[PDB]
Length: 493
Ligand SMILES: O=C(O)CC[C@@H](NCC(=O)[C@H](O)[C@H](O)[C@@H](O)CO)C(=O)O
Ligand SMILES: [Mg+2]
Ligand SMILES: [Mg+2]
Image (cartoon, rainbow, N blue to C red; front, side):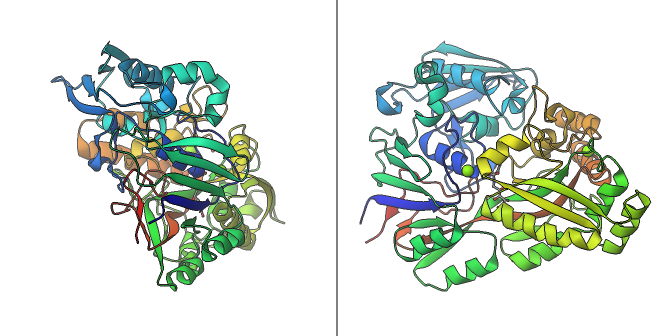
């Protein structure tokens, strides 16, 4: 049939298409269409078990698994005429990914010692110690994507809006705040895409997005976490709703160094007046689930019994009075305008009033909000995300003190947590599998009991499409929790 795909997303604009910085779901989704990596998750899977060849046609490790040699596919071409992808591009990209001055994801690569071009088609990666999940680090997510040395060196600060990858689609143009026009990479190494163009539309307003989808302007539209939207879409036999793994866990990360939240009783009071099970029941159990820990349930090392504080708003009021707040606590939070996070913050705002908290929400456009929270501008941060499914990733990034906002090594530790550093570090390199699991669980119990963060629900990604669109594979998951459009995506007659 037709070869042009139109999709409506919950975003206001592009922030960065440099894969070493792209963090919002929208920027990560675009990056997943433009770039590739040495290896990749199988299309339609978010599980590292599925990892398969991408730019690297084969690889091997030495006996001690400290030296890995990747053999590159010969004639993989960059978009825009930058020529053949070489080992020098891989060295440049991985060294950039592992540099805290040029990447938002450098901490994931701390165990890489060196990356060397043995020849134009051979890359040698030497590790400081064994890294069981190395292939996930080298895959098509976060810092694994490969970029062109020549394009980045020249474009510099403009590369983020004029990206160049070897993926199936290229950015032809950006219409700021309206859309991104992507076109098929005619030289894509797996074959020319069946789609000729993608019109990626910024439709943050849910009512306008739904109207564009029902009027036939969109072939795909991002949904939300509400079962009511899910039921209204599934009612039309022409629509298909995809619920996409991994589930992103939402937490209230509390800055434990800032009064009044430096008193554990105040944090405990907040935790006793949130009700994640009620949010999950309201939003719907197919897409949403309350999580009994501070990392997503789909993690090796997840603790189903971390000790999450129960709902008891009478106890919240008692604790606030003991802490010197007989008339309650008021707090202003900088809150994202991404509709799912905005509606979640509004649900929490209503819940916490029962226990004596009056939450004032200062709304900020999503990408601007991401910048503000990373400047330590909010006392509490409602953040929702998933990472590779090994506890070390979520724990290190959100809760290890090295990740604390304000440090050169900062990641997403908005709570300024430091209570679990020794357990996180010991678990990371523990070779006894059961002991490693127990150290990850001990870290979760400490973070929960000190109330550095309060878990809410985790939600699968929700997207609607017309049944005339075929992905070319089963869309079970995608690391950004969004559809993956590839050279296989097609329309039916
Ligand atoms: O990877 C990251 O660090 C950020 C993840 C990215 N995910 C969107 C997100 O927070 C979730 O969809 C979120 O769980 C809300 O919509 C909850 O209703 C973000 O754009 O903020
Ligand atoms: Mg955005
Ligand atoms: Mg902590």
